[PDB]
Image 1 (cartoon, protein in one colour):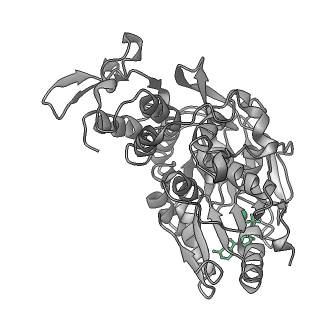
Image 2 (tube, helix red, strand yellow; image 1 turned 120 degrees about the vertical axis):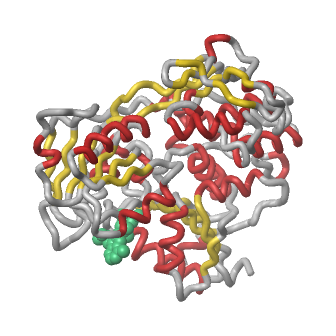
Length: 430
Ligand SMILES: Nc1ncnc2c1ncn2[C@@H]1O[C@H](COP(=O)(O)OP(=O)(O)O)[C@@H](O)[C@H]1O
Ligand SMILES: [Mn+2]
């Protein structure tokens, strides 16, 4: 039983090798036999729901939101959200994180907490991913050979050219840098008669169900589909681009304009296809190169904001997982909030659905969750626009006010659904 060894192992078998569907159940059955207190961390509820079916026969308990006889299963974000709530930790001695490449703040924080527990000698851990931090190979092994081709990939709706895009009779997954860009690409495809499904973080649960059927031609998805999303596809079109949230001078979050993805992201996007060992010839068409410039990526600082507010024995604060710990301009403990503000901080993230950085600014200012005056009293440059006109909301006080938050985070108004959500928050609807 290697699982009792207080160590952290990175299971880095190539995409499609069977980490999720074959190795994970083998580990789980060994953990149950050795009577370990085990948690399985899936990146998304969709993937967690899939795991709940595969582990039907085993004593696995899916936690939507007894320790040695039952294995707990939850999302990365659910695990981190629980670490933030007021009681003592659940005290697992084996952590299994699947799709451990996920770079959203809750996943980064979870890896930091877990790796700290291992360094304390209190647990073992397995991080499953073909693309651990520092990977520089965008073209890893696959179950069947992949036809890789560099081509110009449309960044924009097109009315001519790019016949190879629509002169395809199979199923295509197209990775776009943003929801807004995906909306434009999807509309262009639909207009060419294609059946298109769009995926983003906010819509992933409901919309992914559509992809399990025969009747679609394109999936247009942001990077969220890098996290264990399974498609019956024969082609991936990759913009090779993403947006990067960047904190400027500790004062505002901008979404840096579409820039090259990391090698890990490129490998995971390409890794959607070539998964059938008896079906060669899946295509990966990519439009540009990769880059590693995540030193100013807001997610690792946001992860430190989360970890600074997870309370552990004797006032220890967890460090980031070492291979990704050099990427952050933050000192351990500097974002630690006192009890009620930490409560407000969590509320603004969970109930308010605000980005970590924005929730932190509001909470550390001593503002209570229900007090929305900060959404309207910001500096004039923070005015949020909507179809070239200042956005306005009706408040619960019966006032029509211009949306002008005291702190500006571009993620609250980067697409129509985000702006609609933030307007409802500013209006006091949740
Ligand atoms: N619903 C399914 N039914 C049958 N096979 C599947 C299903 N989903 C995935 N597979 C296949 O199982 C194999 C292992 O996949 P997986 O364990 O997800 O790989 P990894 O986690 O290492 O990327 C792959 O060939 C994949 O195509
Ligand atoms: Mn997997």
